[PDB]
Amino acid sequence: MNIFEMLRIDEGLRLKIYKDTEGYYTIGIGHLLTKSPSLNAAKCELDKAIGRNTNGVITKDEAEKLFCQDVDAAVRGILRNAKLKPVYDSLDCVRRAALINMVFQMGETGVAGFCNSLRMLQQKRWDEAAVNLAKSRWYNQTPNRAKRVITTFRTGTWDAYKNL
Ligand code: NA
Image (cartoon, rainbow, N blue to C red; front, side, top):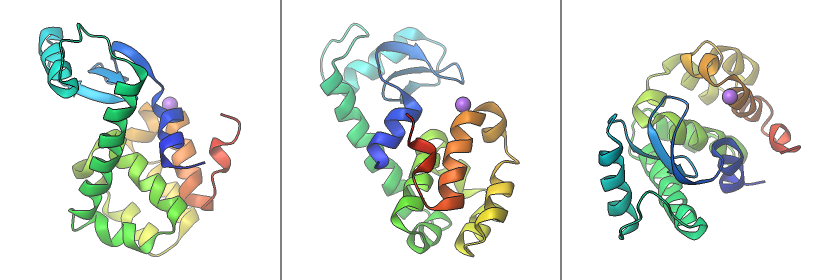
């Protein structure tokens, strides 16, 4: 298991524009296009992102290319955020993937505001961090995904991604 496979499980793969769990136009492996309610706006974002007139449909290779960029962007956002970087640097490679996963889903600013969970992770108080992470809109709105990510933080293993 690795970060690409883990996010592929959590995000799925769809080749036509769809609405994510929050109702926002998305494509590929969880590539958010826009928060605008305008499908036309989403279509401009998509054509700009891919570099051609897509008419709302992309190939698997194109989806994987956006995904490569989006994983990089999540790592970069962690490294450039003064609250996230020390936590990331303190973590092992598997738990780093759990943090990248959170940032991919909700953005650097949102994750960076969880000062109690971040402190517990930095302190390596894994059970306490796991309990604290579940007291979130994130957990309530996407509980099965959040449970997998939380198990990854709690155990430092990929066990939650094994039957998928
Ligand atoms: Na879920």
